[PDB]
Length: 153
Ligand code: HEM
Image (cartoon, rainbow, N blue to C red; front, side):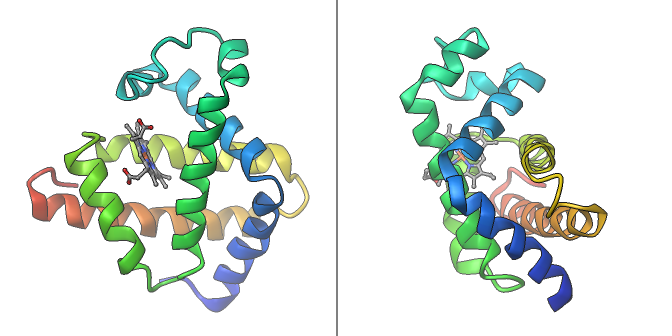
């Protein structure tokens, strides 16, 4: 569990991801798609995209970024108590989208990368540590639901 000090670091930095949701969203997913191209095979809708310029041009992608970041944000603000917001996500990514838990590790990487890219200033080592910790907690609790369902962590 994170301390109050550590949640304050995470949300104090999210309050500025929240400043431009759509720019952040778009950087994160392009980062994911280029570092692990096998993830793009999960969206039939983004399979046509083949270059980064195509990715940056897609209004559909940008729209999926806002979705991902709005869901994430809602979980983060619930701090240590986020089971209401977490469960539907894990059932759908587990059972609908067939997303392995390894990809959520990939996208947390993506997320920390971009935050450091856009905020070499609120995202020092202490804030990097908090954020790591919040994302592992996210992954841990997801993997627990996956386990239950037979997809397990
Ligand atoms: C930070 C982690 C993630 C968040 C917060 C997130 C959240 C969401 C949300 C809210 C939706 C729409 C409603 C629902 O189906 O739950 C969604 C759909 C989807 N997600 Fe995620 N997601 C995450 C990670 C990913 C990853 C890593 C994959 C793929 C490698 C993935 C693949 C998809 C696909 C296939 C859809 C269905 C809609 C579409 O075709 O884009 N998601 N996700």
